[PDB]
Length: 53
Length: 55
Figure 1 (spheres, rainbow over the protein chains, first blue to last red):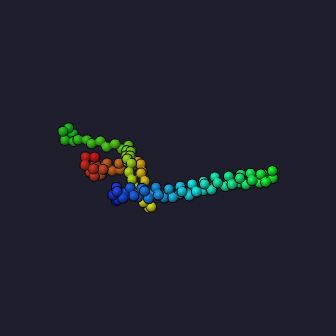
Figure 2: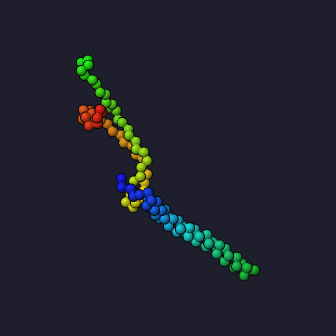
Figure 3: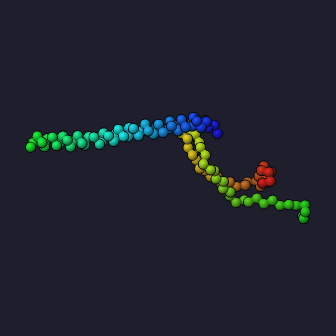
Protein backbone atom coordinates (compact mmCIF):
# COMPACT_ATOMS: atom_id res chain seq x y z
CA UNK A 1 0.00 0.00 0.00
CA UNK A 2 1.12 3.53 -0.84
CA UNK A 3 -1.67 5.58 0.69
CA UNK A 4 -0.99 9.28 1.28
CA UNK A 5 -1.21 10.60 4.85
CA UNK A 6 -4.60 11.07 6.48
CA UNK A 7 -4.43 14.87 6.43
CA UNK A 8 -4.19 14.97 2.64
CA UNK A 9 -6.59 12.02 2.39
CA UNK A 10 -9.25 14.41 3.68
CA UNK A 11 -8.41 16.74 0.79
CA UNK A 12 -8.63 13.87 -1.71
CA UNK A 13 -12.11 13.00 -0.44
CA UNK A 14 -13.03 16.68 -0.63
CA UNK A 15 -11.93 16.76 -4.28
CA UNK A 16 -14.15 13.79 -5.14
CA UNK A 17 -17.07 15.40 -3.30
CA UNK A 18 -16.30 18.56 -5.28
CA UNK A 19 -16.74 16.66 -8.54
CA UNK A 20 -20.10 15.37 -7.33
CA UNK A 21 -21.15 18.86 -6.22
CA UNK A 22 -20.15 20.22 -9.62
CA UNK A 23 -22.59 17.79 -11.22
CA UNK A 24 -25.26 18.69 -8.66
CA UNK A 25 -25.06 22.41 -9.43
CA UNK A 26 -25.81 21.85 -13.13
CA UNK A 27 -28.65 19.51 -12.18
CA UNK A 28 -30.19 22.22 -9.98
CA UNK A 29 -29.78 24.82 -12.74
CA UNK A 30 -31.70 22.62 -15.18
CA UNK A 31 -34.31 22.13 -12.45
CA UNK A 32 -34.69 25.89 -12.10
CA UNK A 33 -35.12 26.31 -15.86
CA UNK A 34 -37.75 23.57 -16.11
CA UNK A 35 -39.59 25.08 -13.16
CA UNK A 36 -39.54 28.69 -14.33
CA UNK A 37 -40.57 28.26 -17.97
CA UNK A 38 -44.12 26.86 -17.37
CA UNK A 39 -44.91 29.74 -15.02
CA UNK A 40 -43.99 32.15 -17.81
CA UNK A 41 -46.29 30.26 -20.18
CA UNK A 42 -49.13 30.48 -17.67
CA UNK A 43 -48.63 34.21 -17.13
CA UNK A 44 -48.59 34.73 -20.90
CA UNK A 45 -51.91 32.91 -21.24
CA UNK A 46 -53.34 34.91 -18.34
CA UNK A 47 -52.44 38.29 -19.84
CA UNK A 48 -53.75 37.21 -23.24
CA UNK A 49 -57.09 36.27 -21.68
CA UNK A 50 -57.16 39.58 -19.81
CA UNK A 51 -56.65 41.41 -23.11
CA UNK A 52 -59.53 39.46 -24.66
CA UNK A 53 -61.75 40.36 -21.71
CA UNK B 1 5.47 -47.82 13.86
CA UNK B 2 4.78 -46.73 17.47
CA UNK B 3 6.82 -43.91 19.04
CA UNK B 4 8.74 -43.38 15.76
CA UNK B 5 6.18 -42.30 13.15
CA UNK B 6 3.87 -39.35 13.76
CA UNK B 7 1.04 -38.27 11.46
CA UNK B 8 0.03 -34.80 10.30
CA UNK B 9 -3.41 -34.31 8.76
CA UNK B 10 -4.01 -31.76 5.99
CA UNK B 11 -7.57 -31.20 4.79
CA UNK B 12 -7.90 -31.50 1.01
CA UNK B 13 -11.29 -29.77 1.01
CA UNK B 14 -11.41 -26.27 -0.47
CA UNK B 15 -10.67 -23.61 2.14
CA UNK B 16 -12.29 -20.17 1.99
CA UNK B 17 -10.37 -17.07 3.09
CA UNK B 18 -12.23 -13.75 3.28
CA UNK B 19 -10.65 -10.30 3.34
CA UNK B 20 -11.99 -7.50 5.50
CA UNK B 21 -12.73 -4.02 4.18
CA UNK B 22 -9.70 -2.26 2.71
CA UNK B 23 -9.09 0.79 0.56
CA UNK B 24 -7.83 0.71 -3.03
CA UNK B 25 -6.80 3.57 -5.31
CA UNK B 26 -8.14 3.65 -8.87
CA UNK B 27 -6.63 5.49 -11.83
CA UNK B 28 -8.39 8.77 -10.95
CA UNK B 29 -7.43 8.60 -7.25
CA UNK B 30 -11.00 7.54 -6.40
CA UNK B 31 -10.75 5.60 -3.15
CA UNK B 32 -12.74 2.35 -3.07
CA UNK B 33 -13.52 -0.08 -0.25
CA UNK B 34 -13.39 -3.67 -1.50
CA UNK B 35 -14.57 -6.91 0.10
CA UNK B 36 -13.32 -10.07 -1.62
CA UNK B 37 -12.90 -13.77 -0.83
CA UNK B 38 -10.57 -16.45 -2.18
CA UNK B 39 -10.94 -20.23 -2.39
CA UNK B 40 -7.81 -22.37 -2.33
CA UNK B 41 -6.86 -26.04 -2.22
CA UNK B 42 -3.63 -27.86 -1.40
CA UNK B 43 -1.86 -29.23 -4.48
CA UNK B 44 1.29 -30.89 -3.09
CA UNK B 45 0.76 -31.85 0.54
CA UNK B 46 4.47 -32.39 1.24
CA UNK B 47 5.46 -29.11 -0.43
CA UNK B 48 2.70 -27.23 1.40
CA UNK B 49 3.73 -28.78 4.72
CA UNK B 50 7.34 -27.75 4.12
CA UNK B 51 6.63 -24.21 2.90
CA UNK B 52 4.40 -23.34 5.87
CA UNK B 53 6.02 -24.27 9.17
CA UNK B 54 4.05 -27.18 10.57
CA UNK B 55 1.40 -27.03 7.85
